[PDB]
Length: 94
Length: 97
Length: 148
Length: 289
Image 1 (cartoon, one colour):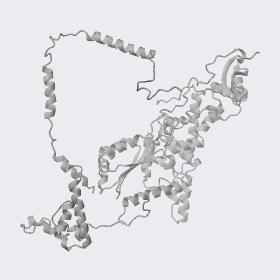
Image 2: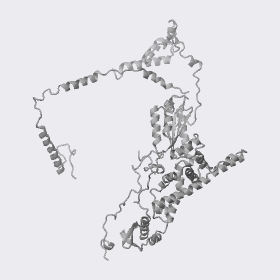
Image 3: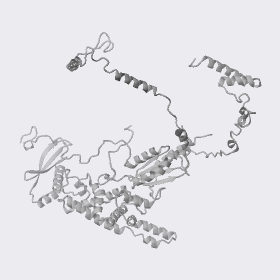
Image 4: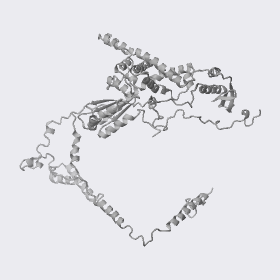
């Protein structure tokens, strides 16, 4: 006897749904977490000047690793043991 | 999907009969034979198919060129229709244009 | 599906494992083929493993028949009276050895969905709840409305 | 006309399964089936229970008078000369008697030492229950004693299987001292008593009179039936709890559908405490000295 014209949550008339005390709790909890976040995000150990190139040694080597990893790709060695090993199918017990 | 209730007679094949035992006997004829007769000559079959290959269209058009005028009216006609169908199906249809 | 099959509660045969463990596998009978390829794995297991397996499991009898047969099978038989069939057909030696080692340590009780993980007797030690257990007693066992 | 051999042949297996379903096969001796070596079985039997038998005595143990009588029937009707070497077979009679006597002696000592408060009739009935046709038949069946027994009529009727089983015991008593056979009996017999109640195997139908007798014997005066809790008296499903009082102390209490059944139950409980068979009693010891 009460309708919600169209689709429930979409159009220019929607279902009225109210905010609840639970939802307020959750929102505030999450805020408090963020506040504490930016407090700890505020104070760097090194300055911007001090941190220049502080590892350029490692970051070159990481990339050398990433390169070598690909350089290593070739079709694998094929060995005698497999081709002749296949002959073991006909093995006779006599 | 009703299946056989009675066992068949076990088929005895002697693989040592003349045909299977002689199989592939003259195959190397050219090489071991100081090449004179080439292995194509070992082929016993339809007169337009010997030592030659092709997909369905080539088979049909080949047969029509070689043995065509010795054909019966009906198989000749069906040969013409088949050549037509295969022709426009290979040329005008497919996924890979 | 669990509504398709039967079920059993968790069980031991003859209260096994209480007094002593009695290994439940009784006889083990292989049938291989000396000539045919599908029995290849079954052959090697007979050469290398069967000796050491028999030494390790004094209780189980092991029968081994080469016969003109196309699908190598091993038939386990249990102290329970249960019989279990396997095909060792076209398997490696490590695979035969593994399978036989699975057969060795099973009860022979059927593999079917077990209803609850534990079988208890006398679960109830010190008491078992009944509706009156926690209610207070009154004077002269009088009802709620009664007069004496 | 080139068929599946795989098809027809595979269907042959189904056809056989259906034959086995509509006519159940009569049970056949494992000795008559394809894989059998009797000496290997005998040796293995002993090896898997960790017992030392002179194989002579064990072979003696599985021989029954029935097997001998049938062997003589065949020796007479086929004109075959058997008698001497067949009379040398030495049936299990002596071994079975040794077995039962020492077995009952053993159990009786076990219960006597475990539950000091049981009356003569009690240890009598318990022993009678562990040695009962049913229980021994069961345990014997599961140890593959039925399979290894030589007798006519392969289903091997219970009175046979029992003899056969105790024959093994006597045979152990010869090879190993009473100390070893003690452990065996307490392992494969006493365990059958796990979970079962006292008056389940007593069958005594007069709980009240027996309770009064035991209380008189204990110099305890007056068992008094008193009604503790009851839910619904007018319902098709009433519930009663009768307590039993000896000098204002509550000796036991029980549930029921009527006042009578409740009395009986409280009596059972009292009897259980007095005699010592209770849910709280220590589980049976297992240790190997």
